[PDB]
Amino acid sequence: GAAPAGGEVRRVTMYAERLAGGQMGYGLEKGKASIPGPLIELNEGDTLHVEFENTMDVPVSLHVHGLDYEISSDGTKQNKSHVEPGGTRTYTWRTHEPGRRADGTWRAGSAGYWHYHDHVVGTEHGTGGIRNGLYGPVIVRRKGDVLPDATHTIVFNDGTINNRPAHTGPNFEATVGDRVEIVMITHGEYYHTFHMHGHRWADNRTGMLTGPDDPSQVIDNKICGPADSFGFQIIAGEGVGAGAWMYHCHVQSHSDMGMVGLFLVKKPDGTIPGYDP
Amino acid sequence: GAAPAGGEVRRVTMYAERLAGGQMGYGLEKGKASIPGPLIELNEGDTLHVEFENTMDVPVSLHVHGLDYEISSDGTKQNKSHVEPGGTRTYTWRTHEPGRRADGTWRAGSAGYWHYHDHVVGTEHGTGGIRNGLYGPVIVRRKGDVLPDATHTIVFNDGTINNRPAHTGPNFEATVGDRVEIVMITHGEYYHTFHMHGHRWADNRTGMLTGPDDPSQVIDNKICGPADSFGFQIIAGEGVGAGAWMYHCHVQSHSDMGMVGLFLVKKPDGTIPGYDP
Amino acid sequence: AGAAPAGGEVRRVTMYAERLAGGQMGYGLEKGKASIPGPLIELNEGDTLHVEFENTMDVPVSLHVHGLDYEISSDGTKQNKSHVEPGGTRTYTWRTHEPGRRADGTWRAGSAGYWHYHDHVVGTEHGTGGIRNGLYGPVIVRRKGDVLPDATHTIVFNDGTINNRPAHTGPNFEATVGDRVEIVMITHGEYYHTFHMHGHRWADNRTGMLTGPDDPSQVIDNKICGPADSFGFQIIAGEGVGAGAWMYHCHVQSHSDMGMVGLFLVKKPDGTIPGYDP
Ligand SMILES: [Cu+2]
Ligand SMILES: [Cu+2]
Ligand SMILES: [Cu+2]
Ligand SMILES: [Cu+2]
Ligand SMILES: [Cu+2]
Ligand SMILES: [Cu+2]
Ligand SMILES: [Cu+2]
Ligand SMILES: [Cu+2]
Ligand SMILES: [Cu+2]
Ligand SMILES: [Cu+2]
Ligand SMILES: [Cu+2]
Ligand code: NA
Ligand code: NA
């Protein structure tokens, strides 16, 4: 599968809602908010109209990295781009293809692994909102990009993965040979290093080398800090086989205190060697 | 415009001077020291003789990243290349173009976003001098590099931008369509993440993709540590329009305590929609 | 300079985990000769390595490698019981592969790069004690045609030490002007660092050297790194700058002030170093 050329005007509804235990999340339908928020996928050239509604009792906003937006969709109190309690607003995101500018230089396209998050809860930089769970992934694909069999989002938010209690994953399941896309986002106060056992990727836009001329370092460990985002695709078990393959932050106290999960790679018969749950 | 081939021998006078409040700065002329220090620009092949004078009552030095220098211009006490109080010294920086060696390998040129700083005030690694403001940017351009309409230097020094009081910018002004160059240097004890709203750049030498075959990640958020330097050029307002575009460190406590500033992008008539400080 | 050949050899080596002085712990290829960092392993893409491993200590230990191909039975974790009991033995197998076009037209990245191995089970189930104690070492996998160096030096930022040495004690590395010197740089523990080399620079890519005039990788002399990061590069000692005692150090200011410093001692042909007075 390959991404097509973009150019569609898409729309979606988004809600900010309180969740259990002081948390807050984005959802695409009322009562269905999650942490991380829903995955938004666009092709270069697509436009996205996000009909947003704040269902909480405190102001919230929606700020996006990487994509084109006018200052009116910045999502900050400073620009009156926030949403009052009960309020509604339409945030508009646009994307563009790469291309040669009139001045002769190459204009980078929108394609990449991006994310959106709150910018007004607790502070005017969204410190409380991000801590509470108001973040989500955005993928913009370029014409011809390889499409995956599954996509999984891993957010290192302070000392947690996806706001979960320590030592509770998440885990992700695949079958040997699956083409698996990982979106990796970092938030909060701390730097982290993301490590995946049994697998590696290229440190470039897609995480895949373009061919024999791409000099990007191939890695299995990557330092990241607050609001960094990257992504990659792997072939599950390629050259290594089935198994419970760990991923974790490699900062030693962070892995010891529980930012660890499993990439559960199954044989075609659905079983995982060496793994007792 | 485009950078010419280099090869000139250039001279400049530089002074280290005390500034108000225990600060120290470099300057091109007596009594005009600034933090950051003056921007030095060279073309690959140029030689620069810095006629240096220490107007201060403590030793100071000038150490440069990236450029060619002999051990006698290292700027360290260890090599006896510091400057005594009231003393003078000529620091020589050289640069070179890339090219094929005899062994067939490719020698990397000097071009890049670099910086200079003190190496002896407070400690033999310049911890006091750097804290006090003794740092500045150097740009070395390759023949053919695109030249910007303006260059702005942003230094994350511990918990400050350019040693400024918290919450005091700096702000930079441009018109929609301007080609704006940012030089980004980090110093001190902390890691940071630099983020720009509404704009993005390529993670490579120039900050611009060379063309459709360049696989560098396109980003708007970059982790950086002490003595890191990078730079890029953006088209102000490209695809997003005029506005007060924030830049800040994205480490949540840092943005909250005042590591924030504004990229004020004006329409040709001078208007900035919705700006209201 | 020499060039790496195509790989595909099947090799075997013995490795031991051993206690060292001061509560330290190290890997070695011969009994009683363990070192921190552990021995440098070098493979050409396509090679297979069978590590006949023996744990001579009184605690379970493991061998976990980054980047290379290994089956789950060579993961080196308690999770899948691939650690080594006290006094026990185990064969760990590492494989590597060349890059190539898959049948579906996508490009498979090869194994080549700067990698490392370390313990994963001493103290905690992530090897916090083992790594702190010194159980780490470098692995280089070369691609056919990679340029070969005159010498290779490994620098590990482990917590606030270099190579588990006492503060301010280097290590120093010696070269002659013109030498092709390879640096392998590994980070472990709890802290981020920035590695800086005076007088020298490299390209931020797989090999540390630009492939030619079309490579847009940033050329740098300073690089941020965190726990279990690894990278490497080659420089021509003294190129364009001459002989001297060229410092390298973490550039986090308090780390350089506390002793995360060392010297790249670049000598004239007559063996002397101008300005270097110890
Ligand atoms: Cu912001
Ligand atoms: Cu972490
Ligand atoms: Cu953000
Ligand atoms: Cu230094
Ligand atoms: Cu910061
Ligand atoms: Cu932003
Ligand atoms: Cu420095
Ligand atoms: Cu692990
Ligand atoms: Cu350090
Ligand atoms: Cu330096
Ligand atoms: Cu590891
Ligand atoms: Na790169
Ligand atoms: Na990087």
Image (cartoon, coloured by chain):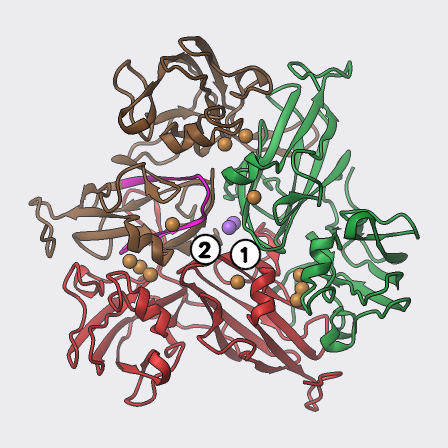
Chain colours: A green, B red, C brown
Asked if marks 1 and 2 touch (Cβ < 8 Å), the reply is yes
Q: Residue at x 65, y 72 (%)?
A: A102
The residue closer to the viewer here, A176 or C100, is A176
Horizontally, residue B118 falls left or right of residue A132, namely: left
User: Which of A83 and A24 lies nearest the eye of the viewer?
Assistant: A24
Residue at left offset 46%, top offset 10%: C90
Query: Which quarter of the rendering shows the N terminus of chain C?
Result: top left
Coordinates of residue A49 in the picture (x, y in percent): 87, 62
Q: Residues in magenta? A: C181-202
Judge whether residue C259 can be spotted in this image.
yes
User: Which of B45/C53 is in front?
Assistant: C53
Q: Residues within 10 Å of mark 2 (few under 14, many from 20)?
A: many
Q: Residue at x 29, y 23 (%)?
A: C20
- Residue farthest to the front? A21
Q: CA distance from mark 1 to mark 2?
A: 8 Å
**Residue positioned most to the right:** A30
The residue beneath circle 2 is: C218
Q: Position of residue A242 (x, y in %)?
A: 66, 19
Q: Is residue C271 left or right of residue C186?
A: left
Q: Pointer 1 indicates a residue of which chain?
A: B
Instruction: Kindly identify which residue carries mark 1.
Output: B203
